[PDB]
Image (cartoon, coloured by chain):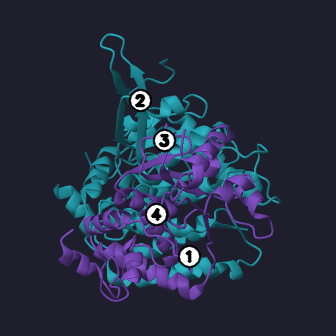
Amino acid sequence: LTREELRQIAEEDFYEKLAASIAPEIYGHEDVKKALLLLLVGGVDQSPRGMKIRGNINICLMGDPGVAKSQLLSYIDRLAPRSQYTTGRGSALVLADQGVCCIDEFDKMAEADRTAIHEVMEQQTILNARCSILAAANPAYGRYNPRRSLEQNIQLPAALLSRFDLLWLIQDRPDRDNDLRLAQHITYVHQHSRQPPSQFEPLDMKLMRRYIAMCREKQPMVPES
Amino acid sequence: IAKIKKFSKTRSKDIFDQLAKSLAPSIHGHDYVKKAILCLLLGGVERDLENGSHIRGDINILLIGDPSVAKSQLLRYVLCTAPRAIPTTGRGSSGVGLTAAVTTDQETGERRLEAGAMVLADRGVVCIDEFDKMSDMDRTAIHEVMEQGRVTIAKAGIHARLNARCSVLAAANPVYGRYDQYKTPMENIGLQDSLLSRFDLLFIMLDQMDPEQDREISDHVLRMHRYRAPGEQDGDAMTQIYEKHDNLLHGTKKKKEKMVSAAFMKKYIHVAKIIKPVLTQESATYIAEEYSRLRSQDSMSSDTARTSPVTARTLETLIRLATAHAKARMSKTVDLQDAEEAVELVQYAYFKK
């Protein structure tokens, strides 16, 4: 980048501004935004003492339909430099090497492909499959039941869920004030064709892509303290 | 042009009532279904944003009810009237028929794309009878079209994206054959939550054998049966805005009202679809408050049950129905009654006792 643009990224509370800059059109869900930002950044890859460790961040987001998961997937597909957006039936892993593989309707896929997904998750190989997997799932009955166990509500094996380093549950809990706030924000987005005015205007997509590219270039070393 | 303007100026609020009333003289009753069909003919507004995100402007309506309630007749009439109408039954066309496929040409060795049923029917109407008989795989295939109006195809050596912005009519029968009054609508419909949510409007039709209703239906059917086209000898084998009154088609009582001609109706529908309405600030707050009331109605549902879950797509459905109603009458802005009609339609469709 031009260092002035990096300074334009590095004001106070820059972490919050970067987190909110990802999909600002969807109100709230700042934790999921931070998780997606860290997935964009990613960890470090090391091969100590004969074994290879992964630095890729794989996140599984499951929630009731209508919580704007598909729009988040489309936005992260747009923003990521190497991104592959695919559906369950419609399928790619190799094509998204050193990138992000955005897949939705994970719960609506046969277990035969799921079996091959385990090797990709565990070793990032198939050929190399060094990619960040972002999977989307839905409850079996269309609504998440807290009475039922998590595995039954996801109808996926426990090992597959464990291989996902982050799990985020979004439930469409009915709250009057939250519903009114969401409705008014949606109406402003429709009428003005723009996001509601927040504290700080989000950064451009190109600037964020370049900043993520530069931050990926560094390999921090973990202190022993 | 002059006749259309005169009819719009004279009949200010009566356009939406008359077009729904004169939609199908051969079919008796079902005013809400006729209003929904009129809204589909008018259509919504497709909006493109600076970021390039696409928002659907089509409406999906599913009709479920007992046999012999004049549902196939409505589908055939819509097929006849719609410019781009393609009929696809449940098991008549599979996912391969509905969704475009890739065929490897032997002459040149390259791969070409052949359009599917929905790809050809761009900005049109697709009618699906016996939707209950359709498999779940075809429903998932249709889900992408119903959500974003696009089909993504990727086979080794070629990849492309095709537009599938279309509206769908679906007619299905209950799982038990006849709708059960005692059992909940969820058991009778027997469909997943995602499919119902993607649908914008749900209508349930009941064959209530009331003496007056039966007498009226029989009289209407009998009058239509005894009718013969003028200019044809009896026993032989085989544009004004208001239609000419007929003693059999209309009746002595209906002499006080006249039906709109088909050609004039088609021209007015096309002109209205050309018109681009703009939403107002006054209606936005009212729609938001009514949406909040609908979401909070779970504690006020009383003994009435809901046919479909209420999600964020309902607000978009409300806006789209308001846009269609604004298209019904030639105007530029959205008024209060414009949203009130859509709210009444939602109240009728969503809640059943």
Which chain does the numbered disc 4 sit on?
Answer: A
Say which residue appears at 68% left-offset and 59% top-offset.
Answer: A162
**Callout 3 amino acid:** Asn
**Callout 2 amino acid:** Ala
Depicted B15 relative to depicted A201: above or below? above
CA distance separating discs 2 and 3 = 19 Å
Asked whether the residues under marks 2 and 4 belong to the same chain, the reply is no
**Callout 1 amino acid:** Glu
Q: Which residue is mark 4?
A: A42
Q: Nearer the viewer, mark 2 or mark 3?
A: 3
Query: Which color was chain B given?
Result: cyan
Say which residue appears at 48% left-offset and 41% top-offset.
Answer: A128
Q: Residues within 10 Å of mark 4 (few under 14, many from 20)?
A: some
CA distance separating discs 1 and 3 = 32 Å
Side (left or right) of B30 relative to A83: right
Side (left or right) of B28 relative to B181: left
Nearest to N terminus: mark 1 or mark 4 = 4
Asked whether the residues under marks 1 and 2 belong to the same chain, the reply is no
Depicted B61 relative to depicted B47: above or below? above
CA distance separating discs 3 and 4 = 17 Å
Q: Which residue is mark 2?
A: B156
Q: Which residue is mark 3?
A: A128
Which chain does the numbered disc 3 sit on?
Answer: A
Asked whether the residues under marks 1 and 4 belong to the same chain, the reply is yes
Say which residue appears at 24% left-offset and 81% top-offset.
Answer: A7
Q: Which residue is mark 1?
A: A224
x, y percentage for residue A134? 52, 56
